Image (cartoon, rainbow over all chains, first blue to last red; front, side):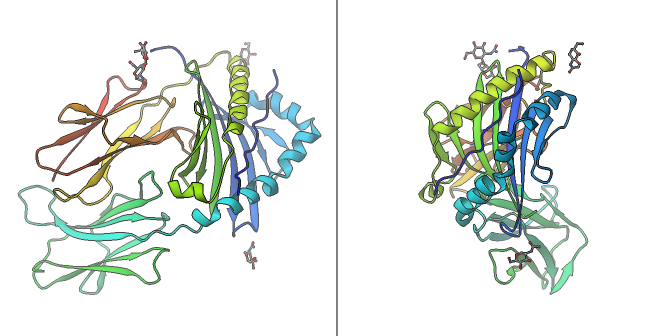
Length: 13
Length: 191
Length: 179
Ligand SMILES: *[C@@H]1O[C@H](CO)[C@@H](O[C@@H]2O[C@H](CO)[C@@H](O)[C@H](O)[C@H]2NC(C)=O)[C@H](O)[C@H]1NC(C)=O
Ligand SMILES: *[C@@H]1O[C@H](CO)[C@@H](O)[C@H](O)[C@H]1NC(C)=O
Ligand SMILES: *[C@@H]1O[C@H](CO)[C@@H](O)[C@H](O)[C@H]1NC(C)=O
């Protein structure tokens, strides 16, 4: 089975 | 190289209690070592940890898509990944190798330490006890503590501060999840 | 709790170093070799049971780079304070002459995640047989790292793990010899 990554959220410029 | 450095870290954490019955997810962001903003599944929204994180908490919380993506992570990320890896992580059991040998605090002394070296085990939780003639010795016990080897094994040395006498039987006893009963190693001065 | 799984990432300027790894209860499950775009399982057996699309990690690191730029500005360019490492050398098993063993150099409690580590045998650098881990996360958000040297214990050889870090005034040498 495949491990899933959690995305990192882009911050406010 | 004396140029200033700047570090960003992210830790996406899944905390499991009683298998996957209770799961907590944290989405954590750091500048150097300072956590500045975090999503805690116990709350369900981002919260600024320091003033540095306020703009992110405010903007991210305004986006329902971000919030629902994070709110579902306990299931789609944590529980999913636990299922993928549990057989070789959660279920990993490697039994310790146990060695007992005498030692000396200073090189020209007669033996005044007994060392129980417990090596190669997984997971980390372990209990090591010393006995003299079947009675537990609690005085003069000192240890390295639990040492992680970095390769999915641990070790620990547990010393008993005593001078071995002929006729005495010393036993190091080890309890560990990989074992179904205590592992014992006996040592005698005239063995 | 009972278990913790962490996907830990970092990006460091001006080095332009990024790392992506998974941790289970303090041990590394895998990391991504960002240059080769390959998943590197900590134990070979792990990869027979699970997979991870390495390509995916590059996107996260790119976001972390962008976020670092944002946070650097928010902080008015406040740089990281160097925290020098604690270094320990141990063997993985009780030492017996002429019985193969492994020296472990444990580099702990440091930041930023940049180090130069050299094994020395009788004062000379060793590269044969050596291995190392990537930078591993600590709960206090500093780092740790392991280096390894398989060896045949002898009365004739002495060893040192030499560690260089910007937080140190000079390289730290931790010694090991038989007895
Ligand atoms: C580790 O050693 C290297 C080599 O000294 C240092 O990195 C730089 O290496 C480049 C070439 O690859 C040189 O141009 C630089 O002069 C080196 N840095 C310096 C001394 O200015 C690096 O600093 C060392 N890392 C440490 C000590 O953490
Ligand atoms: C732990 O798991 C068992 C089996 O599902 C269950 O009976 C028990 O109530 C659980 N404990 C909690 C509080 O999660
Ligand atoms: C950066 O400087 C500005 C202007 O003084 C200030 O408003 C802000 O709080 C500073 N950020 C800090 C102290 O991290």
